Length: 336
Image (cartoon, rainbow, N blue to C red; front, top):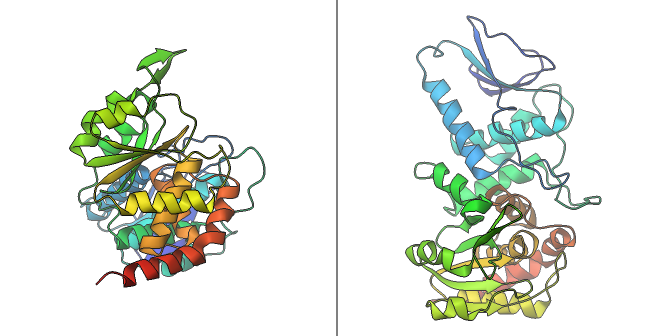
């Protein structure tokens, strides 16, 4: 275990190993590299999504409470594939934050505690270069912030539901802020199957939305269904179009924040994929109202909905952070 990162004195370690190790009477080894696998869009490779973080933490907690392993060092290993290794490092750092009560900085210090190469930064889903480098530390800080503001709770998290509704066959949506924001791909005019691709019409969503207090739909992409189909059914509906892969005007950001601040229910936000444009505007709201940094919210939203926030949208959020924070301080003063 030379070079291994120690997370619990004489008890839990994170190791990078070129070949499969053999568990012994003294050491239990396990890897998730082939069990929890990131589903990529293009050259993005992580971070692993929230349900995969949950499944890891469940796996590890059971090992640490197991009688058969109670006298053993438990070693989470990953390989020399740096894209597997960054996700594996993210997983055990996140466990450290959630269950071992370490700060993101402590968890990350542990990840550097061996003699190991740096961890590769995560990147976006674009076809070019990505110069917004989302690090493992950023992802651990996003986890801490989500925990801090109750955006997830692994005592109640329902991974079967998460894994059900993320699928295009079941509507392709994810909660980003419980009770407040759901992100999804844009409905089509008719529920059907076209070239083996399942398409959902607005009405398909009504039961879930009504049951979960979705009062408002915000569309950010080109119109291919009549807004009336939602408003008839009782939903508020709003159009704030901006071009795929671009950043929204001040006017669009202003309008989005007013729409969301003036409902007490949840807002279902969509674009074409529900990734770039949708993630960018939700990020603006969460930076203003919860004071996430740009790195924390890009991490948090991608953990909930991989592929979210692309290309220039990333540097946009960094550029707008300071003013969104100010606008939030003003907003909260004018309360009371």
